[PDB]
Amino acid sequence: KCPLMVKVLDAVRGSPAINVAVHVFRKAADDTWEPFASGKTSESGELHGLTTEEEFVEGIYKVEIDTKSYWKALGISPFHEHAEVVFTANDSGPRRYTIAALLSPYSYSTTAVVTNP
Amino acid sequence: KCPLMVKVLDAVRGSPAINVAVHVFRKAADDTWEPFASGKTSESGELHGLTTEEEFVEGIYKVEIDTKSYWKALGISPFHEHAEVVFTANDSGPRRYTIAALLSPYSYSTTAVVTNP
Amino acid sequence: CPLMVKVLDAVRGSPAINVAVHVFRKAADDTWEPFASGKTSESGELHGLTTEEEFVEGIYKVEIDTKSYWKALGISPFHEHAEVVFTANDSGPRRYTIAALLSPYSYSTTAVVTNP
Amino acid sequence: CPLMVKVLDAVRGSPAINVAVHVFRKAADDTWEPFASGKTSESGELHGLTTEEEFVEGIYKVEIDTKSYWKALGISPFHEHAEVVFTANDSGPRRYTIAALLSPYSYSTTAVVTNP
Image (cartoon, rainbow over all chains, first blue to last red; front, top):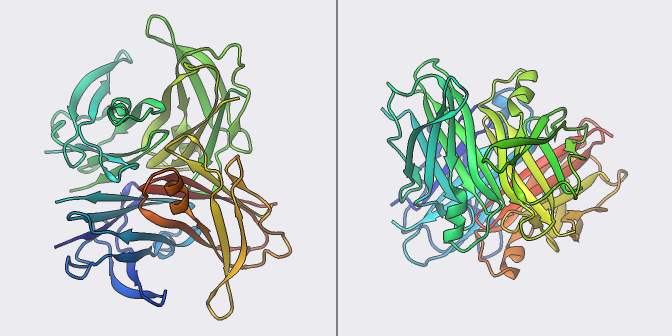
């Protein structure tokens, strides 16, 4: 269905962070990152449809959020090159992962919400 | 419609914070807080239906989240008595307010997302 | 120092300077009584609010005037202030650091609690 | 100190002690080269990673081993580590404080950047 979704918020303007590039990678057996999925956040700051239950197998995944380009479009010079979230997906009942990021120019936070539908 | 909604997340368990009491107050002319609306967060950690466009007039509002009771039910002793969010509602186009809080035992964060539907 | 406040600015990547802070203690009649006040320094810190002798058991409120801070920078922020409410010293004297990280539409606050 | 790391624990309200930190610098061939490493002290801080002379312009990565920290406390956390990637010293020498606030399913990181 939709086992992985990303949401990005802008703490300076109190708004969804729209049109932010997100790249997802999976760790391959040789220890390198393979492209897995990508997209841009919508009007609501969300990115859906990255993958499906069948393809999203147990493994280590990296979600990269292009925060620098977002701030530069606003005319604000930011600190980070990008924000990176690295985690292991574990089967253990049916799981859905929501990765949220809250952005400021010199600070971000990220939270995972993991639920069973 | 639904111009004010509250969402609460648990950073320790990576889950919605369920069954958390929330009280909303409005500042009255004599500078005291009058009860305005209340409820408990749902399974998804959200609280909807607090008020309507007609009643939600410009003013200063306080949202109180009973965080202490939440942690005590989990067996964790927390720092704060509650979390409080105080803000002015301003008419300026149609506005919807989402107040989010992310809870840990010794730390919380709160963010406002303000959008036009 | 039994009670110290530290405030950072997440937009500029700097300490938040000249931020007004007011501290209250809940009195017997359930009212907030003024306890101490001050402004953050160039390092974003506020020291010297109280002493160990005066800082007795109780419920305290630390109010940080975030709105005035952002307005002076030309930004119209969401919150009127940030308030932190906590019980202090109920298992004996501790040292409290209250940190706040500020953005115009969001803030976080953390307590670090040490046993002398 | 040109580069300092500070790590706090939001579950316990304390500094995060004995946290491994590794720093890398992007080399000419676009690989991450090891630059410095260490562990946080009893105050949650890591000092002495580098010097002004060695800390030249570049893209740096600070990796904080959050997973090992939580596991030693009996908690199975979400993230493998926290990584902070930034360009340093491109308008001249600055001093950098990288702070991280940790919870098992969430973290925040802030930079405070000062001009000597």
